[PDB]
Image (spheres, coloured by chain):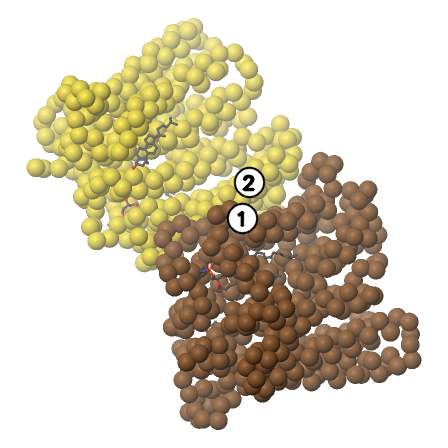
Chain colours: A brown, B yellow
Amino acid sequence: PAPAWTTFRVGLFCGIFIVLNITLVLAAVFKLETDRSIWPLIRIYRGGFLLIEFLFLLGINTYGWRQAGVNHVLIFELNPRSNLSHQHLFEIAGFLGILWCLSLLACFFAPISVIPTYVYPLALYGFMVFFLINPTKTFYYKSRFWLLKLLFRVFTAPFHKVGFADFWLADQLNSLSVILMDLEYMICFYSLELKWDESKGLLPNNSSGICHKYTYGVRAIVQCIPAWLRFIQCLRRYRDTKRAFPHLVNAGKYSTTFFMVTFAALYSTHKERGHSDTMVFFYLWIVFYIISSCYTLIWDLKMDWGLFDKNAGENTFLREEIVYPQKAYYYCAIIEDVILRFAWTIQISITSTTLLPHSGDIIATVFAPLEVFRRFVWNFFRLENEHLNNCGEFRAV
Amino acid sequence: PAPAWTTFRVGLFCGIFIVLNITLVLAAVFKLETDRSIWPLIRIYRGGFLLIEFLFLLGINTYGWRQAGVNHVLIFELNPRSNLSHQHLFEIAGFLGILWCLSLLACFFAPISVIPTYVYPLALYGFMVFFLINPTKTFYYKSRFWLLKLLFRVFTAPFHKVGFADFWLADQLNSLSVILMDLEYMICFYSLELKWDESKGLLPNNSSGICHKYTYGVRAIVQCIPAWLRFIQCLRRYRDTKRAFPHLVNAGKYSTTFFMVTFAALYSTHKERGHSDTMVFFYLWIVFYIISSCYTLIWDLKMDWGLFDKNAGENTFLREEIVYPQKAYYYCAIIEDVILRFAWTIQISITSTTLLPHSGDIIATVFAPLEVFRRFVWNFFRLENEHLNNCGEFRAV
Ligand SMILES: CCCCCCCCCCCCCCCCCC(=O)OC[C@H](COP(=O)(O)OCCN)OC(=O)CCCCCCCCCCCCC
Ligand SMILES: CCCCCCCCCCCCCCCCCC(=O)OC[C@H](COP(=O)(O)OCCN)OC(=O)CCCCCCCCCCCCC
Ligand SMILES: CC(C)CCC[C@@H](C)[C@H]1CC[C@H]2[C@@H]3CC=C4C[C@@H](O)CC[C@]4(C)[C@H]3CC[C@]12C
Ligand SMILES: CC(C)CCC[C@@H](C)[C@H]1CC[C@H]2[C@@H]3CC=C4C[C@@H](O)CC[C@]4(C)[C@H]3CC[C@]12C
């Protein structure tokens, strides 16, 4: 257990965060002009929010692995004597949340001299970078170095051998692609959409512009960076092991992401010019996003977790040896993993008709956190099945 | 050590309290009308503030006794297996501070329907009562019962035998008499000064009234309730032990409080009628408040702590066996205890000439909080000397 002050700091930051969030809500309800546009701020802060909300759930994941004898430290190939318990993750998440809440509160009131308001969204992320690559031996220097080595080995060519940490982080990126998109948005917005002379330009000067729409495919390209990484890693694992089934079908699972993304982007772009087969590119997209979903869903239950097993009839469609205490848990997860993997059926269908303007954005940002929550649920069973089945073949018996 | 969640709650409440205090400061600077009077609110909330600030320091006192082998549990005659560590006191103080900050913030903004603003100052204290006498077995039921038994044995006649807990609490009340006065103020103000029909009467309807001045001696009487208790307890100890010196001189030390209080009150009251010898009742008061101070100061060093000892020349005017690690500490305390026991020399002298209106109140409430700090310093050495000298004769060898 963390000796005496890590728990105290966890509580301190958790206590500051709640009241800062309530102050944020109240200031948003009351002291907003409701005259100029408001969407750029949401699109810029959505990334930081669902990153802090990713760390806060990874903490609970660590706790859940520890309290069930999973032995995750041996799986990840981590140093046995030194490793981060859940309290350190809670504390880092709380500190980043305090910084994020402060930087967002500083744009609503904007209590400051002539210096503009568009500095806080930048500076915040600057800190989030200058805290990660800090060369000094302070603020978890033993952790960020391993994190950066892993992130470099993942974000690169298949030149490196694939281990469980590489695959795990590359897959976590796959269900986290809103930060990448919602960082390219900030870059492209500060590039050619913000007039620096206006000291309030962070909120646009009217109640649109070419910043978000799929125009030159840059957004469509960045939509699947992680899919590319996982595809290439599966190809490399096959090249090095020559067993076709698992890794080839895995790469097939990710190719559907390429297909769905390109079809959706092409349909959305041809809608503008009013081309002929806008009914076709709308249909075919829906086809791929269907099969892709199925191609993923089965793989989450058959190969990832391994629940629908032939034997273990007493456990009623579970494994023969389960770890977590209460069986009912699994069942709910299944239902949840069936719902939240679909995800995109309700929001395209909510947008059947033009109910209101900025129809797309509001559903898009209410589903991102549920997407990152599905990944928080996925780990509990991926790591568990890895513990007592070696379904990945990383470990050599 | 508190197992896992008491430290977390200490941190949670400490984290909420800081930001609530900053919000209080900002709302006081910005959203106050600066048109009607503001003093009743300060006089009503001063008591809760310097009570929470008393508990928060008693926590550190407990920690300091524990970290020096004082064995305070045997001194107070407490149950050895069950007793409150410093974390529980920190947590109670933090919870009360959150409640107080919320109740004060609810009067500045007053965000509410037609219900008036003068309810929050009442309800707060109501809770502080309905949390202390709670008959259920919840929220430290083992502590408040002993506290109430002790408070009943102290607040009564000399019919009860005097033990160390009785003397200690009765003496702590002596340097805490601002809560009593600043509760009688609330009572006398809600009695005949607040027009209930006005839904903003908590702040008076103008930019005075007979509520604070010494008029019928009620304030002057309540000024020394604790002095009466300590005087009577010393008399009882003498009656039961027949040793004249310590307890008789002790009672002499408290009689000077009666004298100083009555002289000050009589002078302040005769100033109004413009009687003849207003120069005399101003002089004589100053005399008593002088000797009283000395009568206390020596007793804080000679008999209470026991520093100016004949032997122990190497320790340079300290005891022969000291407990606390660093000697220098003692010296500062002495100087501090020489300054803060005087206290009333700067404040009357700051009021030589009419520098500004509400001159008396501002110094009165800026020194209330240091007076309670002098008592936080006094304990560190009173209990220590009790440990290895038995200077009180409670313990029977
Ligand atoms: C505009 C938006 C852009 C924002 C840019 C900022 C980028 C990141 C912001 C802050 C970075 C987060 C802080 C770094 C997290 C450290 C967590 C950590 O150390 O996890 C490792 C942990 C065990 O590793 P140990 O530290 O014990 O290793 C000691 C033995 N070698 O092992 C674990 O239990 C696994 C946990 C790994 C956590 C992975 C966190 C990665 C999140 C970033 C990826 C997505 C960003 C695009
Ligand atoms: C308008 C203003 C009016 C406000 C009215 C409200 C009045 C009080 C408000 C809240 C009361 C505070 C909560 C009660 C404090 C409990 C502290 C406590 O329990 O201290 C006792 C502690 C050891 O006792 P144990 O609980 O371990 O006993 C178990 C073994 N029998 O022993 C210790 O270490 C000594 C600590 C004793 C603390 C004394 C606190 C008393 C403060 C109140 C006196 C002044 C009020 C006028
Ligand atoms: C229905 C939707 C909202 C969610 C349903 C599934 C969620 C709530 C369930 C599924 C998996 C569950 C986790 C499964 C395993 C553990 C470890 C156990 O030792 C403590 C509970 C804990 C930490 C559970 C927390 C709640 C949990 C996440
Ligand atoms: C000069 C004024 C403001 C104050 C000077 C005296 C104060 C600061 C000194 C006097 C007595 C000191 C305490 C004496 C004993 C202890 C216990 C020790 O194990 C830790 C430090 C601690 C807890 C000290 C805290 C600081 C202290 C209160």
Element carrying mark 2: helix
Of all chains, the one bearing label 1 is A
Residue under the point 72% across and 59% down = A184
Residue under the point 60% across and 38% down = B26
**Could you say which disc has been placed on residue B22 in the image?**
2
Q: Does the rendering let one see residue A190? A: yes
Cα separation, mark 2 vs mark 1, equals 34 Å
- Camera-side residue of B100 and B340: B340
Q: Report crowding for label 2: few under 14, some 14 to 19, many 20 or more residues within 10 A (C-alpha).
A: few
Give x and y (percent) for residue B136. Answer: 33, 58
Of all chains, the one bearing label 2 is B
Disc 2 residue type? Ile
Please identify, in this view, whether the residue under mark 2 or under mark 1 is nearer the observer: 1
Name the image quarter holding residue B316. top left
Same chain, marks 2 and 1?
Answer: no
Task: Return the residue at label 1.
Answer: A135
Judge from the rendering whether residue B330 lies leftward or rightward of residue B359; answer left or right. Answer: left
Q: Quadrant of ligand 1?
A: bottom right
Element carrying mark 1: loop
- Camera-side residue of B21 and B181: B21
Above or below: residue B59 compared with residue A193:
above
Give x and y (percent) for residue A3. Answer: 36, 53
Judge from the rendering whether residue A344 lies leftward or rightward of residue A370; answer left or right. Answer: right
Question: Looking at the figure, which quarter contains the C terminus of chain A?
Answer: bottom left
Give x and y (percent) for residue B368. Answer: 42, 29
Q: Report crowding for label 1: few under 14, some 14 to 19, many 20 or more residues within 10 A (C-alpha).
A: few
- Camera-side residue of A160 and B195: A160
Residue under the point 22% across and 34% down = B323
Disc 1 residue type? Pro
